[PDB]
Amino acid sequence: KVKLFRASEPILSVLMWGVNHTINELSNVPVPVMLMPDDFKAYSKIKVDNHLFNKENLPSRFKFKEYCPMVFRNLRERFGIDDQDYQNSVTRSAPINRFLTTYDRRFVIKTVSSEDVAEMHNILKKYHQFIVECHGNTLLPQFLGMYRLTVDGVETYMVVTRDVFSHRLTVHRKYDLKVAREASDKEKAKDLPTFKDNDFLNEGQKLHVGEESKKNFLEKLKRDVEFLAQLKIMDYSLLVGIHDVDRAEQEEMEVEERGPGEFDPSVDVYAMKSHESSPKKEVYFMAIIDILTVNPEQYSKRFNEFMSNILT
Amino acid sequence: VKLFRASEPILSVLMWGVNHTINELSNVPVPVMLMPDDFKAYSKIKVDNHLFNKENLPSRFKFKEYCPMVFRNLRERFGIDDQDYQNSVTRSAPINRFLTTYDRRFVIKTVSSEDVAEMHNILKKYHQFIVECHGNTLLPQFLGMYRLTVDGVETYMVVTRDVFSHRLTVHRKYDLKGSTVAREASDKEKAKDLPTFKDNDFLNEGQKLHVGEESKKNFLEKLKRDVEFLAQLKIMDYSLLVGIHDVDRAEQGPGEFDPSVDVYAMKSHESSPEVYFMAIIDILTPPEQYSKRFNEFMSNI
Ligand SMILES: O=c1[nH]c(=O)c2ncn([C@@H]3O[C@H](COP(=O)(O)OP(=O)(O)OP(=O)(O)O)[C@@H](O)[C@H]3O)c2[nH]1
Ligand SMILES: O=c1[nH]c(=O)c2ncn([C@@H]3O[C@H](COP(=O)(O)OP(=O)(O)O)[C@@H](O)[C@H]3O)c2[nH]1
Image (cartoon, rainbow over all chains, first blue to last red; front, side, top):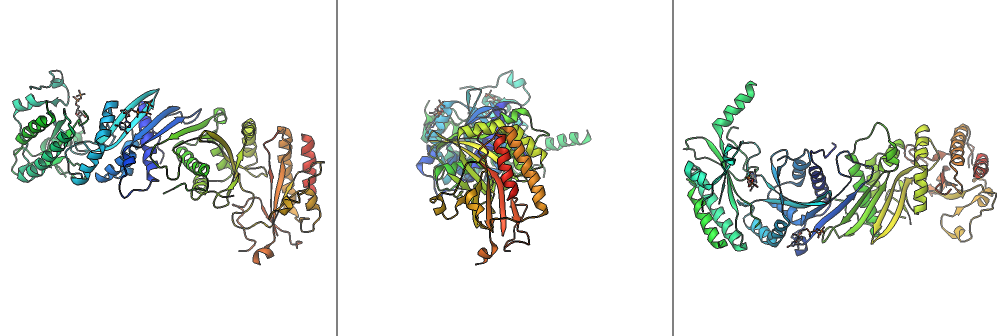
C-alpha cells in the first residue's frame, strides 16, 4: 500500500510527494458551498527539512507550494475528476514525458514560467465562472492544479491538465493549429511529428464528424474564443489528433503474434467519432491549448474561421 | 474529516503533526534492523499556508519528530499499532501542561530541552533494554518525541503509555521515591481531589499494605532489572507512581480489565479487603546509591 515515490528525478519524486500531501491535506478540508474571494488569493506552502531519514527516494530538503488549492479542487470537481483518482494517477507511479504525463496517460503536467502562474491568477475567477456556465463543456485546457516545487534551491512551476488525447486510443497523427507556419524539416523527420498549419493545408486532410458532432463542437469553440478574446489573450492553439482504428487493430495484432474505436466521453472529453459515412474509420481529439500568454479580437475571429473550415 | 479541533492551538498542531508523521511513516518501509543514524535522525516540516485551512490550524507552524524510526520501533516493541496511536491522538482533542489522549490511553508530557538531550543520550541503551526484556518492563514506555514551533515558540513533548486504565477510574494515587530524605504529601497537595501522596502518607494504612504471592517474585525481578539498569545509566530522582481501585467504590464488568491494554494493572490477592497500577516515572534527570535505596523500599511494600 506503500507509496515509495520512486522516480528518476528528484523533482518528480517531490512532485509525487507533494500531490499526495496536498490531496490528503485537502481531504480534511470541508467542501464549501461557494468559493470566497480569499480562495483565489490563497496557497499552501510547506518546507520539508529532514535529517538521516527517508532519504532513499526523497530529497532530504525541499518545498511544495500549491496555488489556490480550493479553486483547483473545485475545478477538479467541475471536471468530474475525483481527487483520489487524481492523486493516484500522479503517485501510484512516477509520471513520464518540460512536458510530462502521469503514468496512466490520464493527466498532463507542464512546467511553466512564473509569468504563466501570474497570468493564471489574473484569469482564475473568470475561468471558474466560465467553467460553471458551460458545465465544463469546453475545448480550453482543463486545469486541475498549479504548483511550485522547490528542490536544490530551484523553484519549479507546474500546471496539471487533462491530456487531450485518449488514455486508451493511440494517436496516429498530431497537428498544432493557430502568416505561414510549417513544421521543421527536422521535426518532420521525428517519430510523432507535431505538424503545423501549412503542412495540413498541403496534406488536405479533413475530419469527418457529421453535423451533430460538428454543431456541438463549433458552438463550444465560438463561446471559448469569445471568452478568450474577452481576457485579451493571444498565441493559443488548437491541438488535433487522429486515431485510425484499422491501424490500431493491425498494431494490436502485431503485438499479439510476438471496444475498437470505442471510447468513453466521460474520460476522453475532447474525443469524437467520425461520421458513420466515413472513408477511414477514425477517432479525433481536439482542444485549445497554450492559453497562458495583432488584436485579441482579430485573432479570435481568425482562429474561429480557420477552425470552422476543418470539419464536415 | 479530521478538523484537529482542540482546546489550545498547540494541541491542534500536535494532532496535525502526529497525524502527518504517522502517515508519512506508513510510506517508509520497516527495516530489518535499526541503524545507528536512526538514533541521530529526525523529521522537520514547516507549514506556512495563507488564507487556507486556517479555521482550526495556524497558518504558520513547525513540527519536528525526533528519531522517528526508533520511536516507531518502540511503538511496535510495546505492542502499539501506529494507526491506534494516531487515532488516539487525532480523533478528538487531548485533555488534562499534562495531557492524555481523548481516550485516556496515552500520556503526553511537555518536557524541557534538557530532558530531550537526556532522552537522546539514553535512547540506544534504552531501546536495547526494551529489546532484551521483550517489553516486559516497569520503566516508562516512550512512543514518540516532537518539537512544535508556533508563533516562533518551540515546545517539546514526549508520549508514553499511560499507567492508569482507559476504563477503570483510579481511587488512590501515590508517588514513591525512597530517598533517605523525608517526602510527605503537601497539605495543599493533600487538598486536591486525587492527592499524589508520598511515602510517609502511604505507610499509615492497611489497604495501602498491598498483598500478592507468586507474581510478586517475577515483579521484583523485573523491578530489579530496571533499577540495576538505571543505576548503570547514572539516573537519579526517579519515582514509582502507583494507583488503587476499590471496586466497591465503583459500584457505589466491575474490576474487569484487559491486561493487554492496562499493562501495569494487577488484581488483589484473595487475602485482600482492589486493583492496583504500578510503574516507574520521572526518569529523564541525571546514584547507584539512590538505586539500592529505592529498590529496597519498593521490595518490602
Ligand atoms: O496575480 C497574482 N495573484 C496571486 O495571488 C499570486 N500569487 C502568486 N503569484 C505569483 O507567484 C509567482 C512566483 O512565486 P511567489 O513570488 O508567489 O513565491 P513567494 O511568495 O514564496 O516568494 P519566493 O519564495 O520566490 O522568494 C509570481 O508570478 C507571483 O506574481 C500571484 N500572482
Ligand atoms: O494536453 C495535452 N496533451 C498532450 O498529449 C499533448 N501533447 C502535446 N501537447 C502540447 O503540444 C505542444 C508541444 O509541441 P512540441 O513541438 O513537441 O514541443 P515544443 O513546441 O516546445 O517544441 C505544447 O502545447 C504541448 O503542451 C499536449 N497537450
